[PDB]
Image 1 (tube, rainbow, N blue to C red):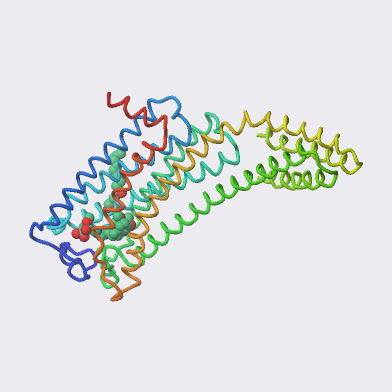
Image 2: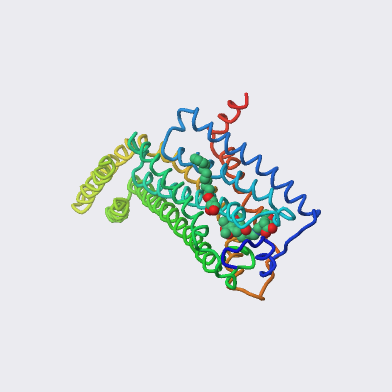
Length: 382
Ligand SMILES: COC(=O)c1cn(C[C@H](CC2Cc3ccccc3C2)[C@H](O)c2cc(OC)c(C(C)=O)c(OC)c2)cc1CCC(=O)O
């Protein structure tokens, strides 16, 4: 059993897995659809890679990482192509080395996209707290990041092919993968799922913080209108106190915004002292000066935040579609070794195609969300 010159039939028969010898009706269609999707992945992801390369506006650290994510899908298109060419009766034709090759290329392609989305999540986590994009230094750093993403992918796709397999542990072979160990699949599934959870936390921290600044901005604009209304001294104080409390929370997060909001804190505190003395008319006039202060920075940050949030939402849709299709397949790996006789693993071909379609979903997402990219795709074809 331990690295014997045994065929794939030996491993597949011992575990509760099917092995065909004849050309089945569903095997012809799963191969037929499989290749058709693979050709589309190798064309749609290649089109968006050329689009970022030729267009001047897409020469930024965030868009270079998107091209690498497409390159990972392009590699996946080649990985699933070799898989679909060796499915059904052609599975028997595979040797021990060639089985680990088709399985290895798929494991490499997943962690290539997993580390890419992880790097994009970190990229968006910095740019939101840094307001705008970085300089040329980051573009040189992105090249280094791309190397780290692909190096991690090659290593993660080599770990089961460098000793961690049930070849010399034939009794601890999984029902789904007859050459892969149960201990590896439990580790692999929990590794990719914990990465999905920490990525959700990263965007939840971004959306939560954006919501907190907009809430403080809503409190600042609403209470400003209250002071404008001819009311008593007590009505002016309660509005300014609500503004001072909103400005201190907005402060918690280059030196332009850090020393920008504190100017408003000073102007509100000076307007508050006027109301405490008894000067209601002077307090309303000082609050009118706060309106001209905020109107000077909305032309420097509010116009640029809309383009940032438009790209941020697009990224979450790419990540969202990735979780919804890959999680049932990864949960299936856990139920394969930790749930014996509770449920049959019949839906194995369905979850495979579900994750395969995602490699084609990414250029479709950028086509209807990104305005500049949608016009660039037509320029290449013509
Ligand atoms: C193709 O048509 C099938 O019918 C078919 C199905 N299989 C079995 C496995 C699919 C499961 C469904 C699925 C979907 C998404 C993620 C994981 C999983 C596991 C597959 O070997 C595999 C194992 C993985 O874990 C290591 C992963 C990963 C990376 O998590 C993997 O990436 C999708 C794919 C094999 C075949 C064909 C060969 C055969 O057996 O004759």
